[PDB]
Image (cartoon, coloured by chain):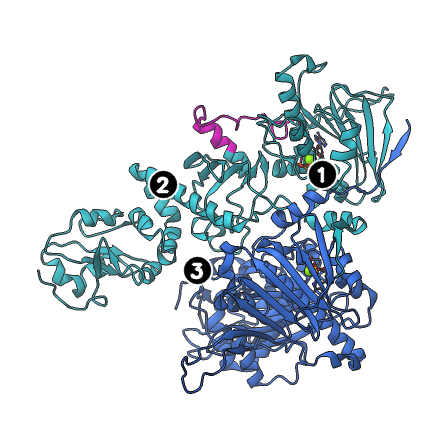
Chain colours: A cyan, B blue
Amino acid sequence: GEVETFAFQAEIAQLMSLIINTFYSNKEIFLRELISNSSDALDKIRYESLTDPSKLDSGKELYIKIIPNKSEGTFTIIDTGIGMTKADLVNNLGTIAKSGTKAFMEALQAGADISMIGQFGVGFYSCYLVADRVTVHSKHNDDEQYMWESSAGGSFTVRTDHGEPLGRGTKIVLHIKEDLAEYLEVNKIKEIVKKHSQFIGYPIKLTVEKEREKEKKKTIKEKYTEDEELNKTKPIWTRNADDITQEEYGDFYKSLTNDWEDHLAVKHFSVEGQLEFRALLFVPRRAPFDLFENKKRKNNIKLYVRRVFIMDNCEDLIPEYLNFIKGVVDSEDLPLNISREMLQQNKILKVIRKNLVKKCLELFEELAEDKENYKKYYEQFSKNLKLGIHEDAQNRTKLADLLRYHTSASGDEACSLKEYVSRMKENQKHIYYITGENRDQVANSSFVERVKKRGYEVVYMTEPIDEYVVQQMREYDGKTLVSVTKEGLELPED
Amino acid sequence: GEVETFAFQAEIAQLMSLIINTFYSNKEIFLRELISNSSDALDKIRYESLTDPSKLDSGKELYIKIIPNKSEGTFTIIDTGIGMTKADLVNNLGTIAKSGTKAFMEALQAGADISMIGQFGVGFYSCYLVADRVTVHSKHNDDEQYMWESSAGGSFTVRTDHGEPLGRGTKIVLHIKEDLAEYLEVNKIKEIVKKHSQFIGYPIKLTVEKEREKEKKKTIKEKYTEDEELNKTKPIWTRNADDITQEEYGDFYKSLTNDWEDHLAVKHFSVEGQLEFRALLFVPRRAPFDLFENKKRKNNIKLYVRRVFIMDNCEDLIPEYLNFIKGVVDSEDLPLNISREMLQQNKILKVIRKNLVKKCLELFEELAEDKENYKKYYEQFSKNLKLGIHEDAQNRTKLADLLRYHTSASGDEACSLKEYVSRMKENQKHIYYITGENRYEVVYMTEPIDEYVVQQMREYDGK
Ligand SMILES: Nc1ncnc2c1ncn2[C@@H]1O[C@H](COP(=O)(O)OP(=O)(O)OP(=O)(O)O)[C@@H](O)[C@H]1O
Ligand SMILES: Nc1ncnc2c1ncn2[C@@H]1O[C@H](COP(=O)(O)OP(=O)(O)OP(=O)(O)O)[C@@H](O)[C@H]1O
Ligand SMILES: [Mg+2]
Ligand SMILES: [Mg+2]
């Protein structure tokens, strides 16, 4: 009875190439991972410095700087973060499948309420996609400066620093590919930062310090690169629901969705228990234009994890009848993918679907009392409610209350079916409805002309989806629907 | 500034914590990877027979079998593939990022016809989405039968198997989670096999327990029956395009879908060279009535990279306006993502899209031979053609003359702009076609999107 047991191994030589060319679709990944790492270092400084402001040595300010070099191709990434030590560069940055989060929580094992993103420890290797050679200038507030460099792809180098010191922070020096030199463009850096690291939580100054060349002499021409409040955007999303202002998160959503106007409704809440998360869920003021292009990339719900952008494929996060929601969920326990792009535990995905649709319908109920807003919401996204009515059976009744329709005395204002419930007559044992293209054509139709003689009211609901749904609601409010095809020319009696 | 160099360092603990929870989208993908691997082994032995049929004596019918068991909560998958060598076992299943498929594909180049699906070596690890304990048995044509037993908990144990005699191939025994027993259903297995492996290239037999009369007191019959109801769609794009007849036509269309109706168009082709991909295209005789029902994912073209379904997302592989053509694309050189769910090298996808657009023009001209058939074509799927007119600019001028039109004057005969251009009228100033939701010689445009069509077709070839 031979028994052989072997530990799990890894063929690394294939593995770095696998990660670089298969884990991450775009070369844009070179920047988001390192910027999030700088954010984590800055939060580390904050947590270690509010306990002892003595560690706030030299420059008290915390920031991130991007310093490209068109002449050289060197991509210098200066930050004022925690820096690196020997142990850091060896284990947290220089080892695959290991991150500084594990060691940091192993040091602070009690009350370490820090939701930092540096958990995977493999996003650092995503730099190869733009840079052939990568270098790191890092200096702790306590440890000396050290140089981490790698270009071989199979071996990396570390040398002691003796020249220009940093004091506080890390200066990541890359070398953007000569063919990929478009990444050296300041505009390209700004755009990739906005799309990947928009809400980091610190001013990424982007302040390229000019390589001054003294002295016929030339005047100053590259006076300053754009240090706009786009990369350098400060954190204002950190406010809880108590001090959140409407216009601030309106501008936050404008930035997130590249929009110009605010959002028509806000919903911030913290669902706890087995699943804990905050959810900055809003609604677009206007419908997305992908109604015709149903196969368009639907990037409406931009889920975040620890203030880091993760999700764009909103199709699997929510049932398609609530895929028009634009907002951010900022969780702290959601199991992501290795590429930080899509959510894997699909039982948890279904749980999230149920909770989010419940919250969205509850908000719509809060949006119900104010008539104009809910009328606008009906005009913009009432169709998804119809589809959920048509095939999502569990929340049909909940959706049904949300439904608004036009009736006889209602004129041309869509009122609830519960308004019809509010005005049935005792003789009526089944609710009168009718389907058609227009209200008036069926209003004068003989189907309800026998009904019109008494001044009765009949539901007038008119769309092809309205024609198909009537099959699914067999009976509403405990009473069957009245139609010349549902019941014929039959006269019920008491 | 002294210099120090690193060695290999990859934390095993977080590795498959990420693999189990941060690799694959849906839990049911576990069987798709298993069937893909079994079919890759089957294609390996098919190539081996093509160069040496003698060794195929260990089994003739290249098929796969599925045995659900709600009683034991176990999933059994037995195939007749190339099997496993213990060294291959360790180096590929027991070692991440090592694929025998990639090595075999790069070992030989003359046999470009063969399909080697899979490139990394981690798809087998998707089995831990639902299986608490995974037990994989296999017997290579050369190596003995060694089973694979591990729970992805930092180690794996293998030894010689002495259980059920695997005559030839692999054998995957699963012990799925108790809360996921819904995946042991016969109907669910049918659904996922038809969605993922209906054109796998080999028989898939799904055995089921059948009713027996119980004492009956006279003759108690057998217990079970074996249903090869799956993959009734035999692989025809592998075969030549000449030997396709209306009976194979109808069988392929009716088993590819579940529709009782029949095809309207066939376009079988295979483009080889720098971009090797085959494709079989089949068009319904009617526009589907569930077109406005998004609960049916818009997955008309199932990209079967190397005869295995990879993912039916039509965001890059085929444009939106080709959402009506339900068919199979058999590529051979695609750079799959780590989970076999998305793709990275988008230039290959773009050139494949353009090639498929040209092939769809060829299909339109193929139906252009039969005026009545092409008339039914256009009056059924006019929406997709006009959507393509709006969307694609590369072939915007090419698609114009391939269109048929029922007009206020042509009656029940569909008129073509190609013929209409051939009799171009000098007095004519604009092409006669007016946007509408539904219905000189003036064409009624069947789509509301046709306002964008008149935006696009301002003039075609001087019209
Ligand atoms: N400012 C920083 N710059 C670079 N690396 C940092 C910084 N702060 C911390 N690190 C370390 O970088 C190593 C991690 O890598 P990667 O760049 O792989 O990040 P992650 O852990 O994968 O997540 P993210 O990329 O979101 O930070 C971690 O182990 C973390 O300790
Ligand atoms: N049933 C099988 N038949 C034949 N070979 C198999 C089987 N299962 C695993 N293998 C081999 O072991 C290696 C395992 O693959 P896995 O299925 O683990 O990844 P892949 O097939 O390499 O690609 P991917 O990661 O995209 O699925 C495969 O590459 C294949 O060579
Ligand atoms: Mg990082
Ligand atoms: Mg595989």
A227 versus A311 height, above or below: above
Picture coordinates of residue B235, whole percent (x, y): 63, 76
Q: Nearer the viewer, mark 2 or mark 3?
A: 2
Q: Which residue lies furthest to the bottom in this view?
A: B218
The three-letter amino acid code for the residue at tag 3 is Pro
A304 versus B137 height, above or below: above
Nearer-the-camera pick, A295 or B372: A295
Q: Which chain carries label 2?
A: A
A437 versus A316 height, above or below: below
Nearer-the-camera pick, A332 or A291: A332
Side of A369 relative to A316 (left or right): left
The three-letter amino acid code for the residue at tag 1 is Lys
Tell me: is circle 1 under 8 Å from ligand 1.
yes
- How far is the residue under mark 2 from the one under mark 3? 35 Å
Quadrant for the N terminus of chain A in the image: bottom right
- Residue at label 2? A362
Please give the range of residues in magenta.
A227-252
Q: Nearer the viewer, mark 2 or mark 1?
A: 1
Q: Mark 3 lies on which chain?
A: B
A40 versus A182 height, above or below: above
Tag shown at residue A98: 1
Tell me: is circle 2 under 8 Å from ligand 1.
no
Q: Is mark 3 on a helix, strand or loop?
A: loop
- How far is the residue under mark 2 from the one under mark 1? 42 Å
Does B186 appear in magenta? no
Picture coordinates of residue A431, whole percent (x, y): 19, 56
Q: Which residue is located at x 75 percent, y 24 percent?
A: A209
Q: Which chain carries label 1?
A: A
Is residue A448 in sight in this rendering?
yes
Picture coordinates of residue A430, whole percent (x, y): 18, 58
